[PDB]
Length: 330
Ligand SMILES: NCc1ccc(C(F)(F)F)cc1
Ligand SMILES: NCc1ccc(C(F)(F)F)cc1
Image (cartoon, rainbow, N blue to C red; front, side, top):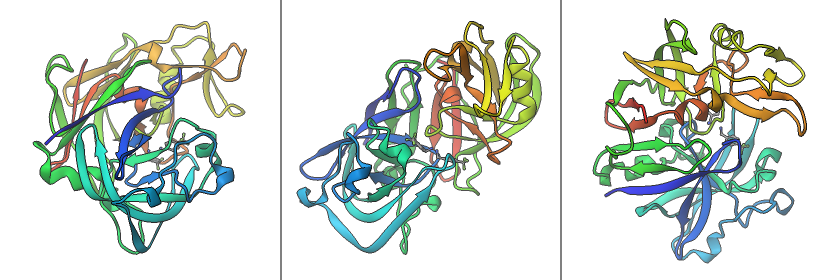
């Protein structure tokens, strides 16, 4: 079987992408943030503290004839940005673009951090990293992808995120009309539970390509591109007036500047991020200082190929027994 669903940016800056997901019987449709950097499927629900819900669509397990409470199970997650949520666990039927999994663990939020409350357009997250990172206790639960794997035509899913435009998540098949040229596959390490791979280098604008190994993770759940300080300094040095601002929390640049492209290596192939993808607009309304889409990973501890990088490519997440990542231009 296969599944295909349209994913849509939540705002004008592509800060995140939401994808409709059907949960329960009869279907309750929630718009979830597909996150290859985490492994929990959690949703706003009728159990969430009322003061922490502000416009989100909630999952109501008592109205689903297929929902079953997972006795004694709890979950608690903390994301790298400081966000967090926690609650109890149900099992229920979950469908993505025609692809149905029965008995999927649906984690019901009882408490969410402020960053989720203020994001009225995200009803929850659908984790697509490896199941070893799932936070359900005392019995760890499997991801949607892991549960669907055996029934998929091919054990893959693909991410085709749009620039200021809708895109597609496909499960079980590779749309050969969605990309140009060939797909270049590269090795994945699962030792940390992430889709972790090694980029072969980078170039700034039309500059020389620098061959250097950059270990990082492919994370649809992170907005920006987080790279080592040496790389990020080399990029912003080519932008007149750009500087690192401690008060803002990263590199900013004059909004009137034109940004150079950024190239990263995948084996012998090259993925080019257009300069416009790196512009994330004024730091505050009316400001002439703009926030950069490439930032340092020094404070994070890991390099993150977030949406800024992934939306420049067609990305294959190959969940075979030896997993690999595929990148193609589009
Ligand atoms: N998108 C989920 C996520 C959040 C944080 C991290 C970090 F920062 F710990 F690497 C990775 C993945
Ligand atoms: N990396 C996972 C993640 C995704 C979205 C959010 C936000 F923006 F909704 F708070 C936080 C953390």
